[PDB]
Amino acid sequence: EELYHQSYDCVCVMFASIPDFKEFYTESDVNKEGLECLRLLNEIIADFDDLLSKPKFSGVEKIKTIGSTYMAATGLSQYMHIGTMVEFAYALVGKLDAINKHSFNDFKLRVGINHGPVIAGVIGAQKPQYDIWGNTVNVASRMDSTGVLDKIQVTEETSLILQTLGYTCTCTYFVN
Amino acid sequence: LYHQSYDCVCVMFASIPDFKEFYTESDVNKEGLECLRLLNEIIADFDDLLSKPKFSGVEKIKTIGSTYMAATGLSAIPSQQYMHIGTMVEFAYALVGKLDAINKHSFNDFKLRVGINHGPVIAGVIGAQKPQYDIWGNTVNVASRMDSTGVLDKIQVTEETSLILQTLGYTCTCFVN
Ligand SMILES: C=C[C@@]1(C)CC(=O)[C@]2(O)[C@@]3(C)[C@@H](O)CCC(C)(C)[C@@H]3[C@H](O)[C@H](OC(C)=O)[C@@]2(C)O1
Ligand SMILES: C=C[C@@]1(C)CC(=O)[C@]2(O)[C@@]3(C)[C@@H](O)CCC(C)(C)[C@@H]3[C@H](O)[C@H](OC(C)=O)[C@@]2(C)O1
């Protein structure tokens, strides 16, 4: 009867998607009607998850995946954790790369990062899911969906905090 | 990669497209918390339909934000008519009626935008951390497309599924009803 909620302020949320994966996936003979593609995707995600085990990213929290899109976040308990999220996205790229050269593919990550206040919480009676709701999230997501392949799009606000840390963000502020 | 294969499963993407506009985070809004409570109320009410014998064959895959994803046909007892496609339409009507009972109690005017499609699907769990089950495939990406390109308060359905629906009794424009 009670809605499980906890508010957090200043959490960096990332939406790391592989926009060309929907084109790749095919279903027919060679693929086994899709099964070969899901295995690759399963391979890609499980490899990304493996980064979470690195002490370097002990503060990163995988929320879940939406299809091939990966959602993570630092801050679920200033700026260090915002810089950690950028290091994690770089780490996702490098893992996607190690996969592209083993599976003979050319996948590219399109990351969208943003920080701010958030409300984590569980919705629904059957099959309850823990999301991160809010505007900083819908904006983190917007950075991704309007982002650029192989690049990390970041809002004007977050770009500054990043500079405070050391990341030179190209001005539409991107980073690599 | 645990996976299973199913042929002919009706998958529905029932979304509330105006909810993103509604949501806000202010003084008179509890920085969003009041909105999540409404959404939590809307989803938990939808889930309550699954308990109806009428929909014992309906299975909730997940919700994506405010979007609800369900499906008939995943019943896994190695049996491989088009009744379960008609069940999915009855379930979407049922989501509308529950959304309505909520609009009149919370003084809102939310509208559901449903996308239904049937076909072969691969249910499976992906990811080491927070592994999550789904329904992958083209019938799914199409069920989804029916939703995302759908019309408020209407159920968009592909040419193929529209026919099966007529075989069952559903009036079909060029949208079930
Ligand atoms: C519920 C609120 C609102 C407005 C804000 C929000 O946090 C979201 O739930 C996120 C961003 C957020 O929950 C992260 C997951 C996902 C799937 C990316 C959501 C959707 O984009 C939602 O939009 C829809 C239409 O569900 C959105 C944007 O809706
Ligand atoms: C992984 C495969 C592929 C190509 C096919 C598929 O089944 C999907 O995973 C669904 C449709 C499917 O898993 C149902 C949930 C949701 C959220 C609707 C998925 C996304 O639209 C995926 O797209 C993305 C871009 O992640 C998509 C379409 O990607």
Image (tube, coloured by chain):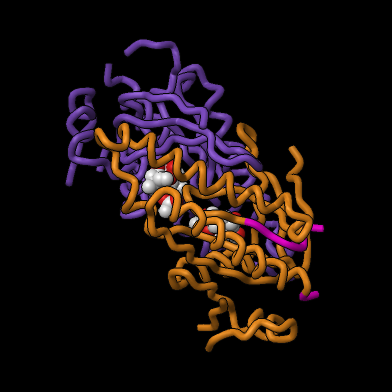
Chain colours: A orange, B purple
Residue A91: image location, x then y, percent: 61, 62
Residue lying at the far right in this picture: please name it: A77
Residue A122: image location, x then y, percent: 69, 45
What is the count of numbered marks?
0
Residue B166 appears in which quarter of the rendering? Answer: top left
Q: Is residue B142 above or below residue A60?
A: above
Residue ID at (54%, 62%): A93
Left or right: where A132 falls relative to B80 = right
User: In front here: B115 or A129?
Assistant: A129
| B140 drawn magenta | no
* Main secondary structure along the magenta-highlighted residues: loop
Left or right: where B125 falls relative to A88 = left
User: Which residue range is magenta in the image?
Assistant: A72-79
Residue B82: image location, x then y, percent: 27, 21
Q: Is residue B74 above or below residue B39?
A: above
Residue ID at (48%, 66%): A110
Left or right: where B43 falls relative to B90 = right
